[PDB]
Image 1 (cartoon, rainbow, N blue to C red):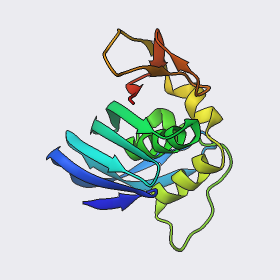
Image 2 (tube, one colour):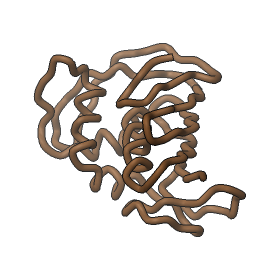
Image 3 (tube, rainbow, N blue to C red):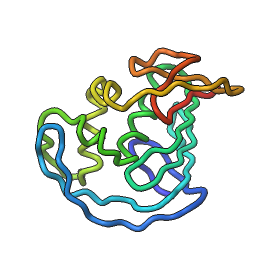
Image 4 (cartoon, rainbow, N blue to C red):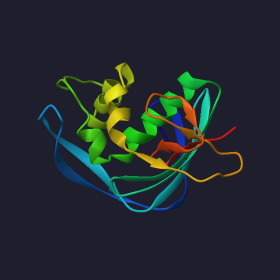
Length: 157
């Protein structure tokens, strides 16, 4: 169990080791980040939202988020997208990432997208979805949809 972005993450299956890696942001800043390598499954519980997360090396496999309102659901999605370490998120950064107490690089990334996530969501990718009991899609602009969704993401009740 650990905490990230105001969410408690508890690992329900799988595992990971960490390898340092250099990466190039969409503002062309180089960062050394600790990459988690492994298939892992988690629950996330924040103050206003809950989720199930399955991921692998720099890849979000599935996120099912349950939340109180649009605002809360969004915050959960942003934390799980940054936590995924996917390169479309790395490449969505605009402006430099300063400092820093307080802030290893994953937190810097998070603080950046928490100030504004529009570009993160635009660039993530969408997919058509099927009908699944208790599950609905969320579009890049955060409105609901039965036909499409942000890739890997679904909203529960």
